[PDB]
Image: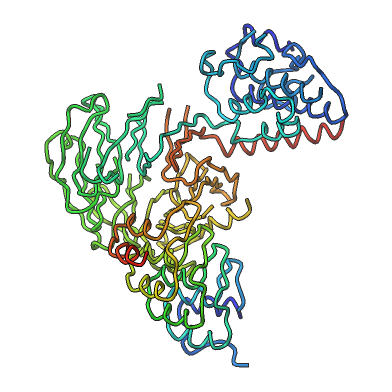
Amino acid sequence: KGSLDRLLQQDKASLTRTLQHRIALHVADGLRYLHSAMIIYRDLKPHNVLLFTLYPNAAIIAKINQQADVYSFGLLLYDILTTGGRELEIQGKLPDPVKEYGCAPWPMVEKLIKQCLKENPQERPTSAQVFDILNSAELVCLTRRILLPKNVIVECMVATSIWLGCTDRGQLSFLDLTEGYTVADSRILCLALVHLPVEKESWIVSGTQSGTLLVINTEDGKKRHTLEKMTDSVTCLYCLLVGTADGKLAIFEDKTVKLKGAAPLKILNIGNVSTPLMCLSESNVMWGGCGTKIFSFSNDFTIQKLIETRTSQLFSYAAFSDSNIITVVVDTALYIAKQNSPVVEVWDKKTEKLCGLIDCVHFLREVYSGRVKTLCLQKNTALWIGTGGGHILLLDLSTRRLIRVIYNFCNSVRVMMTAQLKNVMLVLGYSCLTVWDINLPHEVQNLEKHIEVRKELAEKM
Amino acid sequence: LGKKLLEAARAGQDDEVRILMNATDEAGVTPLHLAADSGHLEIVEVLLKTGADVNAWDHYGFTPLHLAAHVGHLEIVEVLLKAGADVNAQDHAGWTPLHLAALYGHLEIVEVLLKHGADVNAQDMWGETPFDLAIDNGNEDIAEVLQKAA
């Protein structure tokens, strides 16, 4: 049903990203076969692809010097990613795809083009290697990948344009997704957003080690105000809640933020200085942990349940269990991550007792530190787990089984959470920021199934 | 058997001891490893004499000096370098016992290991020395003695 000229000419809308990475995968699965049985092409062009029937979830979508063919395939992949482009052919000086042609960003292909377009016919990747790199979910989705300058390390970030919280003087950096990134004595440990749709203004509030909460708006950084929480290092904000280092938590009314130095509606105390409250999650019942113990809110802002998670030390290491909570995510079961702990436990919100364990290093050693850093929960059933090293873990809450150990192209990972930019991830680590589509694990499963089906068909033929 | 011993060492066998006549686990926890977390003292005086390995690292990679600087102890370290535990063993994240000591503000431990021949130029893939770990957590007191011994 057509040839790969018309859709590149007129049918630009139907060329979705998952379909874009279905032709090149299928072309390189024929080029690999050709070079396997010692053949050459010398005319690999979009004119010789001749798709069968274009729609993503299809078994077959399109099908057709030795190293001079890989250059032509790289040119074809360039003309696939850039839906257009019609002495410069063999020049090695073509413009970057998104730089001039204005295509949607897509790393690990924008780099594959450069890798396969080198002006030296001896080290460009062979077709087997090019197909091997081409088939990968980390390549297919990876919506964006922004890089940050040296010694701009960060440990807190929030969506909306993305606010980045970064020396010994607290400075915050406004990042826009453009892509040109840009105020307290103490460094900003944690940061979160609140929204007031009634007054069509959004106040962005950051926590500092000196405890001087800041009130600024996203449209301009001029109208600035402060609150009067203080008394410790604010470790978590949520929408307004505050979690300090002494276990105290300060609830805030939505409309109190505009007033200068507004008092909390009611100061709630959990524990002592050795127990910091650093995690707050939305289920209308709040959840969170302090030191080593979990609690629960109600509609009148009072603790209802208070379970002790020190009793988890009967399993795993006491050196990990006897630690502060970093983050909590509340599904039907409770997931909390301990400080410098490669073990994530599963807590039952009903029986108030442990019901399972998740060993991050047990998944990691099948593919580098393993110590959990952040937890992310996605929609119905998909769990995202960080790691102290450079790693990303995907889990399936149905069976707690690994989907794919995504390797972040950085030494470590610090903070990640869901976002709505089209729904995307936001993974940040040492410093690089990577943006992934929410459908990453289902995409991994679908691509693996489709590749298995296609391999079976090719073995049949 | 081995599972019962390694689980009870976490709680503390005291009396039960071990087979008057060094099994691992699927998680790789050895009796000394599980024992040095709870920080008992009978553990390393009734099991080291038996012949339990001074260094039998875990899947995480954890000699029972990393654990002793993790939980925070004095007697366990004082005893375990009597046998001659490797003061320069490295975690799978490249943490030495001195690194973990400086991470948790134990001046006593860094003082103990430094006099026993602990280095200060130990390295990880993050390129951080125990001085960096000490300052990053705000425990400049340990960094002072590390600089003095540097």
Q: Point out the image quarter for the N terminus of chain A.
A: top right
Q: Nearer the viewer, residue A238 or A182?
A: A182
Is B99 located above or below residue B52 in the figure? above
**Percent coordinates x, y for residue A65 in the rendering:** 81, 22
The residue at the point 59 percent across, 51 percent down is A401
In the figure, is residue A238 to the left or right of B84? left
- Residue A326 in the image, given as x and y percentages of width and height: 38, 53
Q: Residue at point 21% right, 46% down?
A: A251
Q: Position of residue A290 (x, y in %)?
A: 31, 58
Q: Is residue A75 above or below residue A350?
A: above
Residue A322 appears in view: yes
From the top left corner, tell me how far across and down residue A335 is, in percent.
Answer: 44, 53
User: Which quadrant of the structure image shows residue A30?
Assistant: top right
Question: On the picture, is A127 further left or further right than A238?
Answer: right
Name which quarter of the figure residue A174 lies in.
Answer: top left
In the image, residue A204 above or below residue B41: above
Closer-to-camera residue (B102/A294): B102
Left/right placement of residue A451 relative to residue A293 reads right
